[PDB]
Amino acid sequence: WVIP
Amino acid sequence: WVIP
Amino acid sequence: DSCIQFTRHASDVLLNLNRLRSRDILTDVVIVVSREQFRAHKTVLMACSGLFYSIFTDQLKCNLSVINLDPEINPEGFCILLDFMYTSRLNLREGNIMAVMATAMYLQMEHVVDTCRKFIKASE
Amino acid sequence: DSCIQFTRHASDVLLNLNRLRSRDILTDVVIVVSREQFRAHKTVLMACSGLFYSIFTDQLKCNLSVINLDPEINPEGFCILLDFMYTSRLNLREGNIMAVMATAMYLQMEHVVDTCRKFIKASE
Ligand SMILES: O=C1Cc2cc(Nc3ncncc3Cl)ccc2N1
Ligand SMILES: O=C1Cc2cc(Nc3ncncc3Cl)ccc2N1
Ligand SMILES: [Cl-]
Ligand SMILES: [Cl-]
Image (tube, rainbow over all chains, first blue to last red; front, side, top):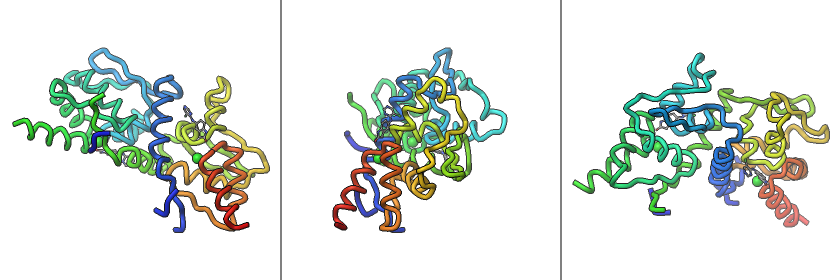
């Protein structure tokens, strides 16, 4: 999971 | 395009 | 093999599937949640959820145009997860994390359940 | 928004759509090429091809279970492109590049047409  |  | 690969292909496909959903094009099922209705594509739901995979591979249920979810399922939690299925983006907030995790557990969306568990553990 | 994003989501969705294709699950159309038949999902074909997008958004054609392609279309070129649609992998070779480019032009798959043009220009 990432900060888009 | 890339070499996978 | 000796194939070449287009890096953005999978993302472009999902973006186009979401545009078809927005415009209600070729949607083939209605998911009913506590009298809230959501139109979607059976194949996308199966590709994202262990529950929908089991439902639409069933010889009788594969032919249904309406699926009713368990009444304990929260419509907002479902809506957030349906958006995630079609975009890879999860709108996870303090106010919805419990409903989102409970819905992801029911839908069998293991990666979503994992990030909810981690976000909850960080707040304790 | 304040969304989080699962990097591998789009790729995992496409991988699952290809597994449904392999097992012939929920395929809703047959594409006929020079008496060679290919089963697929209308939504995936629309997401990948400008030609299929135009065909299945047509009020009469959206309901067809069989689509016949132009007889000049080569079945191997179509097969390579159908595989690309479901995997992001293009099996481009000296022996098939001309048929693949001609099929990608007909199907309106701009990124494929682009790499074929570049690979052909490098060999001249
Ligand atoms: O967490 C998850 C996400 C998910 C998706 C599916 N889908 C499929 N699996 C295998 N072949 C085809 C399909 Cl469509 C099954 C189980 C789970 N569990
Ligand atoms: O090269 C290409 C690839 C491609 C895909 C599509 N598909 C869609 N476009 C927009 N909204 C939904 C869909 Cl399904 C249309 C044109 C082209 N041209
Ligand atoms: Cl997931
Ligand atoms: Cl393309």
